[PDB]
Amino acid sequence: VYAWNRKRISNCVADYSVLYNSASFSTFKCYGVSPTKLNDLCFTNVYADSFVIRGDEVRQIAPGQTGNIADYNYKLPDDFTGCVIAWNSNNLDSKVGGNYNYLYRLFRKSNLKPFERDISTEIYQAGSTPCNGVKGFNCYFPLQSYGFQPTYGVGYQPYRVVVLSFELLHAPATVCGPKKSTNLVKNKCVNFNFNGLT
Amino acid sequence: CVNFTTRTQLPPAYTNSFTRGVYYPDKVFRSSVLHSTQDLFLPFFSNVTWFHAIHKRFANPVLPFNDGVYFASTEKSNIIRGWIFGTTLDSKTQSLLIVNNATNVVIKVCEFQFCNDPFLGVYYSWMESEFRVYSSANNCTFEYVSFKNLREFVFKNIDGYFKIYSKHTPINLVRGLPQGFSALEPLVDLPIGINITRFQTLHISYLAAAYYVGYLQPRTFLLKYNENGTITDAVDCALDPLSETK
Amino acid sequence: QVQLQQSGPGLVKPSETLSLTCTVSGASISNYYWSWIRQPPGKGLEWVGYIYYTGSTNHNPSLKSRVTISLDTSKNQFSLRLSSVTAADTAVYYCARAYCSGGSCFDTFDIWGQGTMVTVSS
Amino acid sequence: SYELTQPPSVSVAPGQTARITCGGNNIGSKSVHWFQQKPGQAPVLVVYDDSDRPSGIPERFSGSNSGNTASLTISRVEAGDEADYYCQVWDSASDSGVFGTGTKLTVP
Ligand SMILES: *[C@@H]1O[C@H](CO)[C@@H](O)[C@H](O)[C@H]1NC(C)=O
Ligand SMILES: *[C@@H]1O[C@H](CO)[C@@H](O)[C@H](O)[C@H]1NC(C)=O
Ligand SMILES: *[C@@H]1O[C@H](CO)[C@@H](O)[C@H](O)[C@H]1NC(C)=O
Ligand SMILES: *[C@@H]1O[C@H](CO)[C@@H](O)[C@H](O)[C@H]1NC(C)=O
């Protein structure tokens, strides 16, 4: 989560029906857009951010939310326009001995700005004495490992989270949703629509 | 990038456009009819600047784009390979790069850090193995990979769309821009959504071709679509009073 | 709820090595400073030393030459060894956890063990 | 060695305010903490960071640290407040915890 990945999506089409009609998502919440209306909207660009957090932290991924993840790992803007999707990944991101490859920023002197990624691993100086890269009192590692295990509770089990931020700026509309066509009938008075020409 | 100690460039040459540069205004078919439209055209009998591409390092010049550029090349082998478009042509701003390597055609919009002397080399069947055009390419915003010959192209950046129209004809003239009528068919429109004010030519180096550059203007034209829809003749509504009557 | 349990010899002969063990239950022994405090009869609390999960250890200057603090994360325990124990070492020994709020471990102790009485008598 | 001095005992009737003082050179520049220890029980943190109370500590307890003196104030002393109160600071020079001599609070 402290190193949440991001991908740009532009100049393409996607059928969001497979998305919001899929039951494989534990959390599916859209702000500023109707989940069932995605195929009906075009956007200049989209950002797909991806990471893993435990269930109890899933609620922090939303505008106006605070907490360790919201403040130090991943922050959303209050005017965020887009959707948040999350689903348990216990079978994938948990291990018998504890999956410690997932970490979250536990120390930070300030909160992250919207869509800010902080990957600094510098020893956090909690006192006046500098740490000089040596752990000790007032000197703690800024990241904390989840150590996910299959026996952890739902709120502690891992969840893969994807945030889709749709941006409809003054640039030409590039990302859209493919509308299914209909069979063609000849020699009958009908209403036609060919690639938008009606 | 490959560095050249001696950088030079041939002086520009000047000629006249005659009556080329016509390209289909829309994607609409008409049959045996005259249609009038006001768009960016290459005005008939315009001043055109032409130069040579040698395949001492003679480097192509960077030229302004203005509102639309008519490019042309007359060569036997495909010496001309592509172009670069933008305003600063550096890493500070997004830059467009179009090329047609031996494999296919590549078009990328990125914050390229272009080389001082863009280089594309071939060695002898001729096989290309040297491509040193840009030192960097970051924050990429677009990517898409697909007896003389006269290859003509028209580039127009309007409404965030870089529109390219093209034509390819077998030309027998040995020197000079050939006089004749041949419409440019649409090649492709790309919604890159960038600003372009200058450009430079991209050539191949064999380990000399000739090209022409003219500039479009907002002009009103009358095209004559044949029965088959081919653009047969055109009239510029501001060349001379006879044109205005037509 | 984190719990600390102290075990060791209730009676140790003079000049022998006193070995006390503190077991942590309900939470991982990691990411916390674990300290030993001794209360001699009739005297106030005296800090003996602390150990961090990374192996960093510090001790009271008056007891540095005789005190060793070790950590066993596999058993979630930490041990205090006092060499050449004397009658002055007869005391109640508690293990305590440094208070860590917001990730910063303060110089206070929030969780204490019930304490174990060690008597040095021949 | 850095030392903290506390009164040996403080007697305050129920309902009154008990003030326990902890003396030490430059203690004002250090974070002073107050622990409560009942007979036969382990010390319990009552105040930290010179004003802060761990969750569950009644509001009647309060801490202050000024100059060379720290003060623990117990408003409305109750029969349950009878215990030994210890002030603890951290000497960064020796990086060690220094505890006060302890004050026996009694409630007649
Ligand atoms: C074209 O422009 C050049 C200077 O840029 C000028 O010398 C030349 O006369 C022009 N062409 C004609 C036909 O006038
Ligand atoms: C990348 O280029 C785009 C151009 O559309 C610009 O808006 C964006 O700020 C650039 N990002 C960086 C990090 O330079
Ligand atoms: C392109 O130019 C227009 C007008 O000068 C300006 O509004 C726009 O911001 C420019 N775009 C870039 C990417 O510089
Ligand atoms: C149209 O094309 C056909 C064959 O493609 C040709 O026979 C015919 O002559 C053309 N029409 C005109 C008007 O040239």
Image (tube, rainbow, N blue to C red):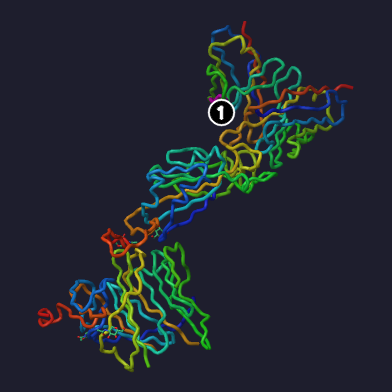
Residue A162 place in picture, x, y as percent = 50, 48
Name the quadrant of the C terminus of chain A.
bottom left
Closer-to-camera residue (A85/C122): A85
Mark 1 surroundings within 10 Å by alpha-carbon count, few (fewer than 14), some (14 through 19), many (20 or more): some
Closer-to-camera residue (A113/D41): A113
Closer-to-camera residue (B77/B22): B22
Three-letter residue code for mark 1 = Asp
Q: Quadrant of residue D104?
A: top right
Q: Is A117 positioned to the left or the right of B168 in the image?
A: right
Residue A84 place in picture, x, y as percent = 46, 45
User: Residue at left 88%, top 26%?
Assistant: C13
Q: Main secondary structure of the magenta part?
A: loop
Residue at image mark 1: D49
Residue B76 place in picture, x, y as percent = 40, 90
Find the magenta span and give its range.
D50-54
Above or below B227: residue A124? above
Any magenta on residue C29? no
Q: Quadrant of ligand 1?
A: bottom left
Asked if the residue at label 1 sits under 8 Å from ligand 2, the reply is no
Q: Is B130 positioned to the left or the right of B215 in the image?
A: right
Q: Secondary structure at mark 1?
A: loop
Q: Is residue A110 visible?
A: no
Q: Quadrant of residue B166?
A: bottom left
Q: Is A98 positioned to the left or the right of A143 in the image?
A: right
Q: Is residue B11 visible?
A: yes
